[PDB]
Amino acid sequence: GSSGSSGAEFYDKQLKVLLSGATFLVTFGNSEKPETMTCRLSNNQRYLFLDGDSHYEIEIVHISTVQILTEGFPPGGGNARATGMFLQYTVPGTEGVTQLKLTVVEDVTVGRRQAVAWLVAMHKAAKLLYESRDQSGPSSG
Image (cartoon, rainbow, N blue to C red; front, side, top):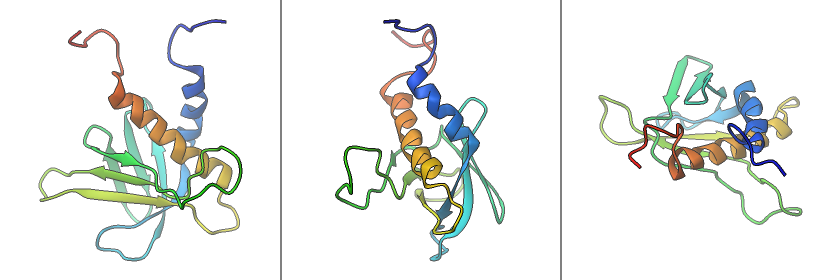
């Protein structure tokens, strides 16, 4: 078996799925109704972008907490069961914290495979981003 040279092929297989961008339902604190938006990662998966009614962007550097909203008990065997998403972040200027929710659209062409795959993928990375460092060198170790 080979350890590796750079990155984790496993985590890399998702990098493509994340960037691709999946459709979800974004709900703003003010808006009570879900709106169809697009969630994708940046070139260096170091920032999140949004496209829709307006130009929105959620910097991962600001994001504090990031968890996935699970309906409940798993329908089948063991998998990345995920129907929704929960992310927390603060904006410079306002007062308090802003959270963003992402759900799977109930349209004919949504791509449950890609969508559900994106959610899990995001969290997965969001874990290494904190649990560990991105670049090995500048660390204070």
